[PDB]
Every structure is written in structure tokens, then in C-alpha cells.
Amino acid sequence: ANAFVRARIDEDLKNQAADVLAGMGLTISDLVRITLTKVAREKALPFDLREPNQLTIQSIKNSEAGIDVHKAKDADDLFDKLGI
Amino acid sequence: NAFVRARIDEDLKNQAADVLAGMGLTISDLVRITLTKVAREKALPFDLREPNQLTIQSIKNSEAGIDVHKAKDADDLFDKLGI
Amino acid sequence: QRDIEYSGQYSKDVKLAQKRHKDMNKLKYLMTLLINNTLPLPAVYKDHPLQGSWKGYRDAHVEPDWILIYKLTDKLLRFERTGTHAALFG
Amino acid sequence: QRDIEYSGQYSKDVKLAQKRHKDMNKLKYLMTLLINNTLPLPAVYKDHPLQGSWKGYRDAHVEPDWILIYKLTDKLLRFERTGTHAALFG
């Protein structure tokens, strides 16, 4: 019936997160239960937990500058150029 | 060395662990990632909980035309709300 | 030129925020951005669709724990609820 | 009609998905919806703005761990990256 989540964590991160949560009436354990409940129900992660990584950001920066960007006329042309 | 320790239902723990294992993660990875986001943003992640009963009741009433009020513009609205 | 509505619950939520001495200008300022179709909202409001399948309903943050729920369609803006995460989702 | 683009990184990511035996119809169908101006996307895609301050960039879920990152403006649709959370965010 009752299990425990046990997770190693930086003590300073833990203190800061606890302070943020305490302002809204939550404990860290409340946040763990709420988050896991959502994951179990949706079979997916909450949105936006991490920033895009270096490779993704580099692709966005290149594309925004017009570097290594390719055009397609429509879906068929696009799938053909991508080989899918 | 510190730890987060939280009591949890065993079936809930197992289901979450299964979802996470499919993405190469443990529950403890998700705990660290989620607490990092909370700490950095000073806010919760979006959409952790469904609207509660009161919120759902209000939406259901409003969609049905129950207890809905009109305002002509912002000044009229603030006037009607008493703000 | 959207029609403006508010729910009965919204008026109650606003009165409660007032009694807690919340800064009513912050809420008013957001409401005005919405009424004037000054969209998209500034990033600080963290504006997003409401969790669940409530079509056109959206969720903006006046503060990290002060939320506004509203419905937005081409023809209508309705102020639905406002309060803490606990009061709206808890 | 929006102009259609894809990044060099996008081409590598689709080749990798293909190599990993992913079901390419799920991705192609979503790409077609975007090309066809099907907005907002069906709710099952959990479509949302990309985390961070990248203007016009959005994030849709082909599967819970298969993400498509794309930029969408009135004039442009660009397919930017696709892959797992670990490949795109990790």
C-alpha cells in the first residue's frame, strides 16, 4: 500500500524549492505526489521541465540566421526531400 | 548529502516508474528535474492538477447561461465588480 | 471588439481577493490587456490553455500563485474565476 | 499558405527516427496537419509554446516521448527538430 520515494538532492536546491512551495502551502512531498499522480494518469511528463539543449538551440540559431534551411513546395515534395 | 523522502501509494509509484523507465528516467531523476524548475522559476510547472469542483461548476453554469453577467466595457465591468 | 462577460463566481472571487488585500491594480491591468485585445500577453503572465478539455478556456498568472481563468473566443471574453492554485485546482 | 521549411538538423533527426524503426506515419500525419493549417492542433498532440524565449517556436507530441519542434508564424512553417526528450532537452 504505502511506499516511499527517496531521491538524492543538492541540499541548497532542496531548501530553495521548499521555500518556494511553502509560500503556496505545499511541502516537497506534496509536489512529489502531485507530479507523480499526473505522470501516472497521463503516461507523460509535465510540460516544459527543461530548456532545449545545446544542439536544439544551435539548430534554432542557425535557422533564424538562414543557415542550413531548406524549402519545400508542399507535403509530397517535403517528404520526398526528407526521404520519408 | 541530502534526500527528499515522500510517502506515496505503491501502485501510483509503480505506474510512474514504468512511464519514466520508458524514457530512461527514474522517479528520483524526475524529482530533481521538477524541484530544479520550481526553485529556478519560483513557480509551479503548468497544469499539474485538473480544475477543481468549484471551477468546473462555474464553467458548467456559465456554459449553460447560468449566473452570467454582461459588461459594456472595462469601466462598466470594474464598476460592476466593485473594483 | 469581443463581448465582455463575467461569471457570478468571478465576482465572488474578486471580493475575496479584495478582502485579502491583494493588489487589485495588477488584476485590473491584466483584465484591460485582455479587453483591448492586446494579445499575445507579456511573457510574465505565463498565459496558457486551461488544463482539461474546456474549449477556449485559458489560464494566466497575475502572480505565481494568483491565477485568472477566462474564456476567449473570436466573439467573447468571459472572466470565469480568480484565486490561488489551491482555490482553483486544489 | 505558409511557406514550408526544414532545418538541416531536422533532416538528420528524421533519418535517425527512421533508423530506430519509429512509426513515420505518426510524424508525417502531424506534419500534414500543420501544413494544412489545422490550428489549433487536435488536443492529443499536447501542442504548446517551446520552453524559453524562442519566438514562434512550438512543441507537439507525436508520442509521450516523441516531440516535434517547429516554428509557426503567419508566413512560415519550419520543421526544426524531432526526437526523444533526451535527444532534444537532455
Image: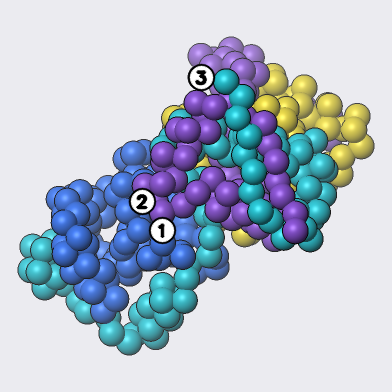
Chain colours: A cyan, B purple, C yellow, D blue
Q: Where is residue C60 in the image (x, y as percent from the top left)?
A: 63, 44
The residue at the point 18 percent across, 69 percent down is D15
Q: Are marks 2 and 1 in contact (CB under 8 Å)?
A: yes
Q: Choose mark 1 or mark 3, whichever is in front.
A: 1
The residue at the point 47 percent across, 76 percent down is A54
- Per the model, the C-alpha gap separating discs 2 and 1 is 6 Å
Q: Are marks 1 and 3 on the same chain?
A: no
- Per the model, the C-alpha gap separating discs 2 and 3 is 35 Å
Query: Circle 3 — which element?
Result: helix
Nearer-the-camera pick, C55 or D87:
D87
Q: Where is residue A35 in the image (x, y as percent from the top left)?
A: 58, 39
Mark number, residue D65 = 2
Q: Quadrant of residue A3?
A: top right
Q: What residue type is disc 2 on?
A: Asp
Q: What residue type is disc 3 on?
A: Glu
Disc 2 chain ID:
D
Residue density around tag 3, few if under 14, some if 14–19, many if 20 or more, within 10 Å: few
Mark number, residue B63 = 3
Residue B2 left/right relative to D26:
right
D23 versus A70 height, above or below: above
Q: Where is residue B23 in the image (x, y as percent from the top left)?
A: 39, 51
Task: Name which of mark 2 and mark 1 comes first in the sequence.
Answer: 2
Q: Where is residue B56 in the image (x, y as percent from the top left)?
A: 57, 20
